[PDB]
Amino acid sequence: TTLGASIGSTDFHYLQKDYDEIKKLNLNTWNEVAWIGDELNSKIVMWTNSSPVNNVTLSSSDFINENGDLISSNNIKISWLKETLANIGRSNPSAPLEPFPDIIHNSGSLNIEKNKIASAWINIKIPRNAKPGIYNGSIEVTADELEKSYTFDYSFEVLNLVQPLPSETNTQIEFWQHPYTIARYYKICKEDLFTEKHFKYLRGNLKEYRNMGGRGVIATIVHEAWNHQSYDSDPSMIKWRKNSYGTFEFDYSHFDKWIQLNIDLGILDPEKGFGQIKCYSIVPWNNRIQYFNEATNKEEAINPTPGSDLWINIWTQFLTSFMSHLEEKGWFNITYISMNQRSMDDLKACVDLIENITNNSYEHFKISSAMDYESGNDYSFLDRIDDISIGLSHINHNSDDMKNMATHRQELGLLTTIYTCTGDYPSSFTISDPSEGAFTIWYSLYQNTNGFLRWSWDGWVENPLENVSYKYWEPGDPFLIYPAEKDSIGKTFYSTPRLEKLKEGIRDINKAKYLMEKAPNLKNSIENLIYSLKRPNKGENAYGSAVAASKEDRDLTISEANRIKNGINNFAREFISLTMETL
Ligand SMILES: CC(=O)N[C@H]1[C@H](O[C@@H]2[C@@H](O)[C@H](O)O[C@H](CO)[C@@H]2O)O[C@H](CO)[C@H](O)[C@@H]1O
């Protein structure tokens, strides 16, 4: 009995603390539904008893449907979930470290020590030319110490509908990227910033971003705009100078290469008007603008207050110059000046100034901002902000205030998202149930917004692979992907279960909206399934980290994710049946 094995949920983590409970498992069967061009995930949870085990390997057979059509084993990637330490933990250095299996790591062998849980992630890519049908296959588990092999009956049904490509949808996704963090971690030099040596470590993860739905691209326009909240500094992609004449000149060099990269990777297409450049921020931390004074040869700073005449003068110089620069590049139409949570005075000042400054064609900068909207009715001010993200904790569990607001914005063609961050449940922390990710995306469509935003693509601590612990926030909050190992030749990042569940959700809401468009007489019933979504309640654990109110609320998150997904594929079956019975 030297090695145990079973199928596990992807909805939650299999930890060491639940070893005893886990050792009693024996799910040998797995069945699920998917579309053509979709993906599915599963997990095989394994354990040892009082002996270590070596070269444990997982094998997938080809998958074959009822008509002999073949999805080869190359479309199934089985990857070890690597464990990493996490204080649990919000702003609390004494709370305990625990391993969490947050990292979708590598294929191939793995040694496991005595008395230890070890899980492998199974990702199944259904090719975009796959035939519909019910496919069948086997996943296998040997080791050295096993003179035998375990077997698992896997089947999935491919429905005769094609998963939309991100560009065929109207889902809006924005995850904030931190290219200088990538530079620090891979030891890229100042002089090699935003050259091909740097791009080699950005390109993989930014393609990952695009292929899941990524549309928004953040770019810093002043120095240290979030006051060094993150482990890494946030340098400005636009360097400010004050010349001998005492007016401000700007060096756009980094911004341009950053944006042009994203254009080259297909995330942004300024000519066709796709994607957003989010410029953070006209209201940076404490209004502090750092600059190199050429006159006094000193690094100096100023803190002009929004509305003040110095403030007006200064941002007028910046915005007028930035506009002209963007118009020369042909990027202006997709550029958004980002604001932040401030007083209505500060915000009214920002919007007044932005709407005043116009090009030769009487058009002004688009505006983006996270906000705190909750109570109904008044849209006179928000109708002036082009893209808004509302935090989860500032959304009412019951009222139609948000849905009406969002719908008003939808009627005018303005963007609206929701976001999660520290102190939210559901959220996308290391300690989260990954399913929370899928819920989150359903909630975005529950509220009739355009989708999801999060601040946390890649804000890595020192060595996230071994320890994710940071002095602020629930652990893993600042990053949805892990870096690869510093010496890596090949991979440049690792994905995570929580990210994979955000992807699932995005794929599934895209299904919903595809059905609504294509089968308009199934629409109202789809909307009813969506609008029947039930929101769980927020608790807090012993150390400041937001968690489910109770286990009833935990299981409700999982429950509802599955519920809406399955219901949505039943609508898919209805539209397919309807089609082939009318043919
Ligand atoms: C958009 C975003 O994620 N912003 C930061 C985020 O800030 C939010 C506030 O905007 C919101 O109103 O209140 C929250 C309370 O915890 C939170 O402060 O916080 C992130 C940290 O998880 C991060 O600092 C973002 O910069």
Image (cartoon, rainbow, N blue to C red):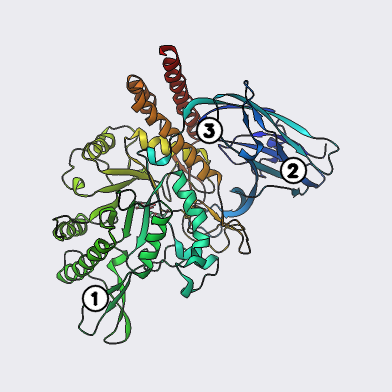
Q: Earlier in the sequence, mark 3 or mark 1?
A: 3
Badge 3 crowding class, 10 Å Cα cut-off, few under 14, some 14 to 19, many 20 or more, is few
Helix, strand or loop for disc 2:
strand
Q: CA distance from mark 3 to mark 1?
A: 55 Å
Q: Is residue 238 left or right of residue 564?
A: left
Badge 2 crowding class, 10 Å Cα cut-off, few under 14, some 14 to 19, many 20 or more, is some
Q: What amino acid is labelled 3 in the image?
A: Asn
Which-is-in-front pick, marks 3 and 1? 3
Give the residue drawn at x 21%, y 78%: 247
Residue 533 seen in the figure: no
Q: What amino acid is labelled 2 in the image?
A: Thr
Residues 19 and 369: in front is: 369
Residues 259 and 484: in front is: 259
For the residues labelled 3 and 1, say whether their Cβ atoms are less than 8 Å apart.
no
Residue 551 location in percent, x, y? 52, 34
Numbered mark located on residue 555 in the image: none
- Which residue in the structure is indicated by mark 3? 129
- Which residue in the structure is indicated by mark 2? 57
